[PDB]
Image (cartoon, rainbow, N blue to C red):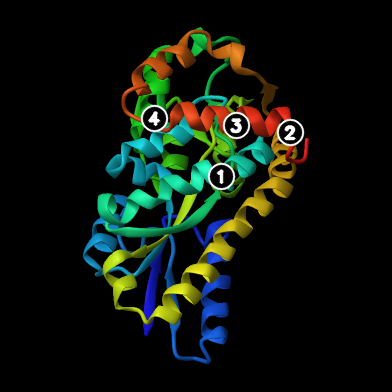
Amino acid sequence: KEFRLGLITPSPHTWTKAAEAFGAELSEKSGGAHSVSVFPARQLGNEAQMLQQLQTGALDMAFMTVAEVSNRVPNMGAFYAPYLAGDINHAAAILRSDTARGMLAVLPQEAGVVGVGFGSAGMRQILSRGAVNSAADLSGLKLRITPFDPILDFYNALGAAPTPMPLPAVYDALANGQVDAIDMDVELINVLKCHEHADTILISNHMMFPMVGLISARVYAGMSDADKAMISELMAKHVDSTLDVYMVKEPEWTDALTKVGKTFKRVDQSFFGDAIAQWETIWADKAPSLPELRKTAADLQAENLYFQ
């Protein structure tokens, strides 16, 4: 079968490369019985549209933000608790935990997809066209976000003016004033060159940003038993591989952003004042897994079960 696999990420992105590597390996492991055609850069629609077509089976596969999935399955919001992870290595360990993996079980019924495992992109950061010396400087700033509620709620609690906007429009929106600031990770600040029009780069690491490898449940049900196992395991391997890329490259992309001539500052959780507490109150009855995920995260850190 010729499967199609969609992403919203551009061609140089880690996820796109992982999807291509997955496709090549599936072709080889299947002896040419199967192939994967990869459609990056939103070619097949926006992420919400892609999820709709995974649900029907019109689209076979995707490497999708957990952000979009959280619009369909609000318990996925638990991953976005601010400062749940202290860094990308902690995040990867959280995403590999039994607690995290258990949360995948609801996806066939709740979203019509099989989630094979988690990957990620980078931690979230803030770029602004103006000076930012305290959280108060974010007030009223039109601030680009990924279109999902956890991040909307965070910026609403901060008093910014969050504005959902897909990746391709962001560079231009900064260049032309449709936004004053953006929420984005270091890989894409580099790749999309969004630092060019910004004044200040804040390395806040305020939220993680998981990815999930999805197979349409309808399509999965049509696979042979051997292929269900082989394809899901192979996809899981490639999704997991992304965690190791970010573990290595996150500080490298971050250091690259000290060489673009802008004001560069690191901040920590205290910078955000009461916004984190407000987020917790919003999400307490939306994402029932949060207390267990917080416990898992705390235990991984206390036991030093990752590189730090």
Is residue 257 left or right of 167 when viewed as pictured?
right
Q: Secondary structure at mark 4?
A: helix
Q: Which of 92 and 273 lies nearest the eye of the viewer?
A: 92
- Tell which tag, 2 or 1, sits nearer the viewer: 1
104 lies above or below 303: below
- Tell which tag, 4 or 1, sits nearer the viewer: 1
Q: Which mark is residue 95?
A: 1
Residue to which mark 3 is pinned? 297
- The residues tagged by marks 2 and 3 sit, at their Cα atoms, a distance apart of 30 Å
Is residue 199 left or right of 108 when viewed as pictured?
right
Residue to which mark 4 is pinned? 150
Counting residues from the N terminus, which is met first, the one under dot 3 or under dot 1? Answer: 1
76 lies above or below 282: below
- From the top left corner, tell me how far across and down residue 243 is, in percent: 63, 51
Counting residues from the N terminus, which is met first, the one under dot 4 or under dot 2? Answer: 4
Q: Secondary structure at mark 1?
A: helix
Residue to which mark 2 is pinned? 258
Query: Residue farthest to the left?
Result: 56
| Residue visible at 70% across and 46% down in the picture | 247
Quarter of image, res 222: bottom left
Is label 2 in contact with label 1 (beta carbons under 8 Å)? no
